[PDB]
Image (cartoon, rainbow, N blue to C red):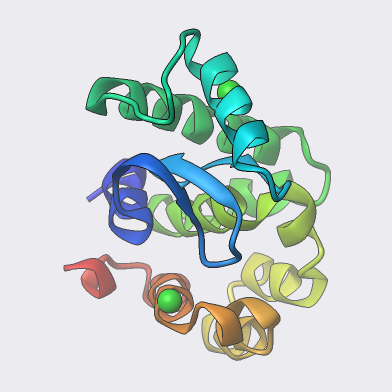
Length: 162
Ligand SMILES: [Cl-]
Ligand SMILES: [Cl-]
């Protein structure tokens, strides 16, 4: 198991424009196209990301490319963020994946806002962090995915994904 397999599980794979849990236009493996309500605007964003006239449909390879870019970006975002970097540096490899997962889903800004949880993680207070993380809109809106991630922070192993 690794970050890619982990996210592929959490996000799934769709080759056609779709709406995410929040009702936003997305495609591939969790690749958000736009928060705007127009399907047109989404199609425009799609064509621009892929470099061609897609008509809202992409290939698996194209999806995978968008995915690698997105993973890369999340990592780099973590590394560039003053609040995140220190946490990420302090974690073991499996837990780092968990943090990356959160960033991929909610963005740098979003997770950097989990001040208290971040501190607990940094202190290696697993169980406490787990409870604090659960007190969130995130957990309440996407509970199954949140449990998976939370369990991964709590145990440091991949069992929630096996
Ligand atoms: Cl892009
Ligand atoms: Cl869920």
